[PDB]
Image (cartoon, coloured by chain):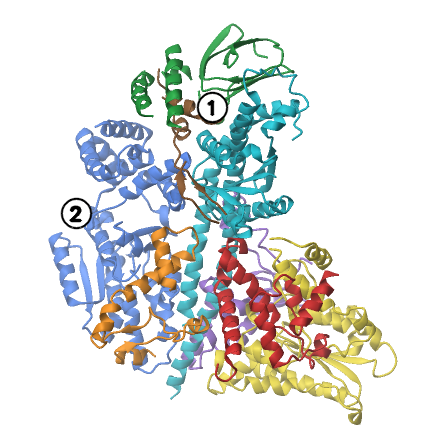
Chain colours: A purple, B red, C brown, D cyan, E green, F blue, G yellow, H orange
Amino acid sequence: AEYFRDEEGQDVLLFIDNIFRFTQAGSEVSALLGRIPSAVGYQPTLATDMGLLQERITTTKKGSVTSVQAVYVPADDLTDPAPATTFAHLDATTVLSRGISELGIYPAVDPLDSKSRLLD
Amino acid sequence: AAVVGQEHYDVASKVQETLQTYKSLQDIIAILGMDELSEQDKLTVERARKIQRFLSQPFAVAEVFTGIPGKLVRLKDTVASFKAVLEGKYDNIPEHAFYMVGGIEDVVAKAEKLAA
Amino acid sequence: ISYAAYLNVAAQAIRSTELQTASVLNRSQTDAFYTQYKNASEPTPITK
Amino acid sequence: ATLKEVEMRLKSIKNIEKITKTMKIVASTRLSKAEKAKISAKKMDEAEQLFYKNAETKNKELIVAITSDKGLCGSIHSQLAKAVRRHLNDQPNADIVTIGDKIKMQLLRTHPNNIKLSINGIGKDAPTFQESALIADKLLSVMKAGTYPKISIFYNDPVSSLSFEPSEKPIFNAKTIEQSPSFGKFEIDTDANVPRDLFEYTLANQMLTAMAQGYAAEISARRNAMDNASKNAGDMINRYSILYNRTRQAVITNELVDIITGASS
Amino acid sequence: KLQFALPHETLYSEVTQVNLPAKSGRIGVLANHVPTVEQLLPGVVEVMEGSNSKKFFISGGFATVQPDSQLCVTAIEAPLESFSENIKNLLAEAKKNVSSSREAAEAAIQVEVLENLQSV
Amino acid sequence: GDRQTGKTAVALDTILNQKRWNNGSDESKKLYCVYVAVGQKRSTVAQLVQTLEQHDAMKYSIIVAATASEAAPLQYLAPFTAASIGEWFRDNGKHALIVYDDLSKQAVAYRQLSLLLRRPPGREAYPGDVFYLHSRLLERAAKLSEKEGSGSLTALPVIETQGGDVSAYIPTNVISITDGQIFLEAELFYKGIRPAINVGLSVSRVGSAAQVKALKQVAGSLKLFLAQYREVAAFAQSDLDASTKQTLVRGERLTQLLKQNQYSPLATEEQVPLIYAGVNGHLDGIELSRIGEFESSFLSYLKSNHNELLTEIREKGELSKELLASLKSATESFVAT
Amino acid sequence: GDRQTGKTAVALDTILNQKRWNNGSDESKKLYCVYVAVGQKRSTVAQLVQTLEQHDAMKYSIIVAATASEAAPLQYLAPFTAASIGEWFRDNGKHALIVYDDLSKQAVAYRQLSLLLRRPPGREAYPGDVFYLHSRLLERAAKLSEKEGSGSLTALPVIETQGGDVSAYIPTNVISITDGQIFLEAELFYKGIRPAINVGLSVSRVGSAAQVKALKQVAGSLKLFLAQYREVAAFAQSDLDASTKQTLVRGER
Amino acid sequence: PTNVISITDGQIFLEAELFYKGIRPAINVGLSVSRVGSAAQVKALKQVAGSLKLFLAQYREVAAFAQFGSDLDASTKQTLVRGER
């Protein structure tokens, strides 16, 4: 993405799949590296590792990457540290719903659950 | 009861029991209203709601922060005040009257204040 | 015997070509009881 | 434990939720039949009222009250009780006939002096002429209804399908029928004792209507109440769900700490 | 119009001719009738709307011609055909009941109903 | 599903049904099943072996066995070892079905190894890379491309829920890794609905993409009916709407119909008729006690009256309007008797 | 208060209002405000800077920065360093303010550092010296005595409660160290109260004296009145007395 | 607690809520068990207290039902009245 933005002067958009699996992957690498796991068994490098990922996605002068990420909420518990840390980085949420799709509406975006930082 | 005297102990026992009832039915109260309580219990609950509120008193070192002039109430006075309340001898005046005030006499006076 | 009670017994007899319905049968059968009272004091809940 | 004690309490709340949902729905079913009946009953009553209006009216008191035996029909029981108590001030010594256990309980408590007749086996049944007739017969014989120069009945008028306003009306004594402004525009027959008959006839016909109006309000109230119950239960589901979730995270962390401490050695 | 009604059911609730059995003997109402109050006795009733005639068995009630040509008939539980043969069987039982049998009044009513059936 | 609710029976049933196609000479109709008995006591595996021999299924069966006694390294490598066996069939372009039963015992063994090797412990005292282990095994199941020779290695892992905790670390991981679940429910099992599949908690994320066309046609309704029956189930608790009563009757009969005696498989050509009756509400007339009698009778009646119909269903694999017409007639006739 | 109730904005407004005070005369009337941004995206910080430069307020404020990108030890040292800068103003006798946004993110940073130093994990996996970390930071920033020239350095540390858990270890430890709370209620935030301040969970345990006398006289007992409003609407959800209704009409309004 | 419970031959559970309820001893009658059981109590006292356990257990069950509301049959209210005493 950075090659496109920085070195080809583009605005691009980079999708990420489960960012739960980003966390999950990170947790394993920590444990293998033998670091003491933190709360709810999540990497002690939890903050910094999300920080690196979520700080190269930014608005540069040249261009901007924008990233649509998928939050596969673990145990649907949004007060879990892994979703929470993700949500801290997130700016907007687009909340596709299956109910909405069942009302024949495609886009599937649930209007009452979609909220964005820029919407002020 | 041998220490604080039988009269105190009896008064305290009744306070504990009433409040414990109120806690027990705290669930039931939330699920269904007060008018769906048993009548005998509903009296206990109404009294207890008053007792609970009665327990608050302004504090004089908090007089700055709270903004309410504190009330120091005699031990002899305290036993009397609760004793009466348990016998419902002042149950007939607002719950607000009981809240954040000193002695029983003060509750009465605040009933007059509220009445205005 | 009260006039509407008089009419009532007649109505009950009246639920007996034939053409019978549940609402009629319910209108002629009741399990209700009436509890006399005095004073507080309660003479029994004699079947209505 | 926290974890299990949370989980079992949340389950209790779930079971409560399920019951309150179920009752509310079943109540709706029951309500439709009740409502249908009340229309037909009211039509009969209106014809009787047509006479009383055109005749005019111009009437101690009797108090009759109507509620169900059944409870949890909202605040029918105590709102009606409050309006009875208000009119028990008005005439102190009046004899209260309580048709239904729930109204029996509130009034009996407030003045046990007045309870002379009370009924039972009201709420379960839908009102029928049979009940009204027998109750009427007992009001006349037992309570000597004509002796009270006022008669008043209390019931719950079902204002809206989601509301109930407790309501009362005055039954006109046999004396009233006699001395009502018009009564001669209708051809009275001295041969018949039309006041003494009509009094009795409207004692029951009015009372049955009161029971019907009340019954519809009662079933409507239970539906309303049980709906609000489901909502209250829902709030508790959410509160204990959050507690469950917090407790769950804590268990994982606390367990993890024990393992780590051991590993460290 | 004519109001002919029961509590749980409601019929015709002035109609052409109504023939009524009353404590005043029998009363006939045809179009406008001068305004009366009459107690209806247990009855065989005819209601005619036009030339069409419908025949009713009535448990007694009250009759009131209103001045505005509203014949309010109110009665408990009625049909004539519904009342009929089973009733003939009942009448035998009812005679037995009259032997034993307020119970006196009940038995009097049973005799009245037996008569009322003979009218059918 | 929940611990020892005869989970192994549900799986074993699938293996038996593969006999029907397997016997068939077309090798695009031959799934050579592999049962991977993990942590199962030798007595249990003896019963398995015996059941397989009894139903003469030991000719498309391989049973990789790591019994309870067998050492924790053997238990650890047991699904992995099994997977390699699957690869030969898959590589040969053949088809096969490998049933890893149960990965919960695979987990315990890895836990034992890691902890004993003093490798860093992790959540729920399960190895840190347990996600990685389970994913490696579960990703070997594959439907090959035609360039790499169309073959497959269908897999159906069986997971033991530790009393119903589907939030537990080993269950949650596995649920994520796989695509689809069939969730047997203990209450149903005890209440005698065997198979005890909880329809609500069963999902397939591939689902109808593979399904006999005929069987798809007559079973869209079935899913929806059961959905209604579940919702209106609790409404049995009185004053019952006519609408609710219609749902209840149709739904109760459907639920009764989907009961099936374990270790008895059925053919698609006999699945399709039974469901047709239920969908068309023919069974509504039949009383609950007589549903069972109806089922076998309907099948025999269909075979006698028109095994032509059955054979058409079998070979055509798609219900034609003419078949649905004829079938309805046959059902009406059967319902009458 | 609760995460992303635009938590930052509540504090930002405090900084903005002091423009009139700061553009005054007398060093006592001037406040010099330091905004410590710990654990915030560079983008978020860039918006803050631009916001401050939009309200032309940049000239009276410092930003000390330890963005999300910046390394975990830098984040650990980030509040302390900022507080040193603040003490220079304070010990110049001048009044000041420091808003530490968010010390909850400092906690996560110290957690990382501690764990990576393999010091035994503490309660809730937050290191055992976490109380010391916050307390040493917090009790610096003060209104000094006349001897010290009546310095001031007001402190507003911005704590991010996880799901509004006010019993949570990091929040409770902070609550006990600090005085007063300005709990930003999520329910109210959703229900359009901006600023959403639940007066029940907001206290100031040393605040009343600080207020100018006018705003003590005029506002007298309004806290009580609106903690009668909470009660009033508590039991609003039997017989509502006319008194209760009057309170409700005033309270809601 | 787990270790000790296994080792010991009875449990005499007390309960804080019942303490507040004013039952002193606050023995939680349902959780309290004696796995060495009756053959240690006075023979007389065994005879009299024969169904006392059953009654109390029934009281507990009835009480739970009673708090889910609704009018209870008279037989149940005999239990309730006895139970209270």
The structure residue drawn at horizontal position 11% and vertical position 53%, both measured from the top left corner, is F54
Screen quadrant of the N terminus of chain D: bottom left
D7 left or right of F57 in image = right
Mark 1 or 2: the one toward you? 1
Which of the numbered marks, if any, corresponds to residue F23?
2
Q: Height in image: B18 above or below B29?
A: below
In the picture of the structure, the residue carrying the numbered disc 1 is E76
Relative image position of residue E15 (x, y in whole percent)? 57, 11
Q: Residues within 10 Å of mark 1 (few under 14, many from 20)?
A: many
Q: Mark 1 lies on which chain?
A: E
Q: Residue D259 at what x, y percent from top left?
A: 38, 80
Q: Which residue in the rendered view is the most extreme toward the top?
A: E51
**Quadrant in which the C terminus of chain D appears:** bottom left
Q: Residue H32 carries which label?
A: none
Q: Do labels 1 and 2 share a chain?
A: no
Task: Please state the horizontal and vertical placement of residue F204, each as a whole percent of the image.
Answer: 37, 51
Residue F241 occupies quadrant:
top left
